[PDB]
Image (tube, grey):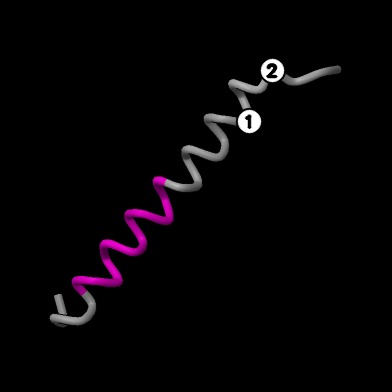
Amino acid sequence: IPSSPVHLKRLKLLLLLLLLILLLILGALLLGL
């Protein structure tokens, strides 16, 4: 069954957002909290 590109877009957006939040916390980690 085909998959609309919008689904893939949201699946990639969610991953990018997760990575952004991860990177954000990896910044706080430099302060210790």
The residue depicted at 34 percent of the width and 64 percent of the height is 23
Q: Check disc 1 and give the amino acid type.
A: Leu
Q: Horizontal and vertical percent for residue 24?
A: 27, 62
Q: Which mark is residue 28?
A: none
Tag 1: Cα neighbours inside 10 Å, few (<14), some, or many (≥20)? few
33 versus 2 height, above or below: below
Left or right placement of residue 12 versus residue 1 in this view: left
Report the span colored magenta: 17-28
Q: Horizontal and vertical percent for residue 21?
A: 32, 55
Label 2 belongs to which residue? 4
**Membership of 22 in magenta stretch:** yes
Q: Are marks 2 and 1 in contact (CB under 8 Å)?
A: yes
Instruction: Name the quadrant containing residue 11.
Output: top right
Q: Main secondary structure of the magenta part?
A: helix
Label 1 belongs to which residue? 8
Quarter of the figure with the N terminus: top right
Q: Secondary structure at mark 2?
A: loop
- Residue furthest toward the right? 1
How many numbered discs, if any?
Answer: 2
Q: Check disc 2 and give the amino acid type.
A: Ser
Q: Horizontal and vertical percent for residue 12?
A: 55, 40
8 versus 17 height, above or below: above
11 versus 18 height, above or below: above
The residue depicted at 14 percent of the width and 75 percent of the height is 33
The span from disc 2 to disc 1 (Cα, nearest Å) is: 7 Å
18 versus 14 height, above or below: below
The residue depicted at 52 percent of the width and 30 percent of the height is 10
Instruction: Name the quadrant containing residue 29.
Output: bottom left
Q: Secondary structure at mark 1?
A: helix
Tag 2: Cα neighbours inside 10 Å, few (<14), some, or many (≥20)? few
Left or right placement of residue 11 versus residue 23 in this view: right
